[PDB]
Image (cartoon, grey):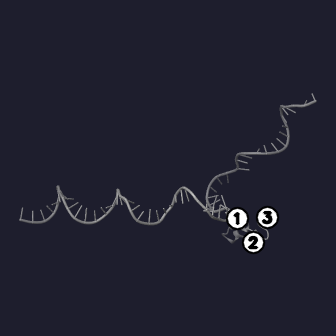
Amino acid sequence: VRERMTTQDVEAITPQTLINIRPVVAAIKEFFGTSQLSQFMDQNNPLSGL
DNA sequence: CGCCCGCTTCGGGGCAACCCTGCCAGTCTAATACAAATCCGGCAATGGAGTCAAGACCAGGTTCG
């Protein structure tokens, strides 16, 4: 945003223009997939799930 | 008078069980203009490769006077 806000022209930008949500959605997806904490949920009885 | 030999402190790299069991990671002026390379799609130089059909012939078991 601060790389974009200074560079582009004033009285033409809008919050849709300044905001790139792609790092946010990529960050959540790379947490949920591919982290050592978001585990494949082990269930072969209810107790192992619990 | 000024000047360097042992602690001493600090950096700084190496290593710390063996089988299984997994399975694929990213973004910001945007375009023209052109020349050469190269692909590629299609007739025509063939030209050689394959193919049919007839035939030449020996002779070798097989048929006849």
Q: Which mark is residue A16?
A: 2
Q: Residue B22, percent across and down?
A: 63, 62
Q: Residue B58, percent across and down?
A: 17, 55
Of pointers 1 and 3, the one earlier in the residue sequence: 3
Q: Residue A7, percent across and down?
A: 77, 64
Chain where mark 1 sits: A
Q: Which mark is residue A6?
A: 3
**Gap between marks 2 and 1, in whole Å?**
24 Å
**Which residue type carries mark 1?**
Glu
User: How would you rate the neighbour count of disc 3 (Cα within 10 Å): few for under 14, some for 14-19, many for 20 or more?
Assistant: few
Q: Which mark is residue A30?
A: 1
Q: Nearer the viewer, residue B52 or B32?
A: B32
From what the image shows, is residue B47 above or below residue A16?
A: above
- Residue in view at x 79 percent, y 64 percent: A6
The answer to whether the residues at label 2 and label 3 have Cβ atoms under 8 Å apart is no
Residue A8, quarter of the rendered image: bottom right
From what the image shows, is residue A20 above or below residue B5?
A: below
Of pointers 2 and 1, the one earlier in the residue sequence: 2
Q: Nearer the viewer, residue A11 or B4?
A: A11
The answer to whether the residues at label 1 and label 3 have Cβ atoms under 8 Å apart is no
